[PDB]
Length: 45
Image (cartoon, rainbow, N blue to C red; front, side):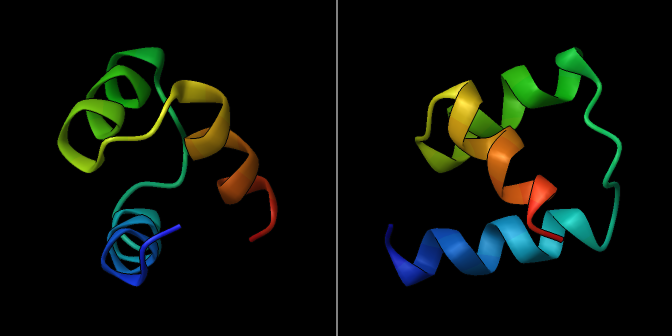
């Protein structure tokens, strides 16, 4: 995990933490992760 990404996950979580599949699809494109990684992370918060 790059810390540059970790900071983008934390920040998007303090904006919206309910992952709509329409927004999960997005974060993955902007931050470069695959959808099961973005989800599991939110779970740890």
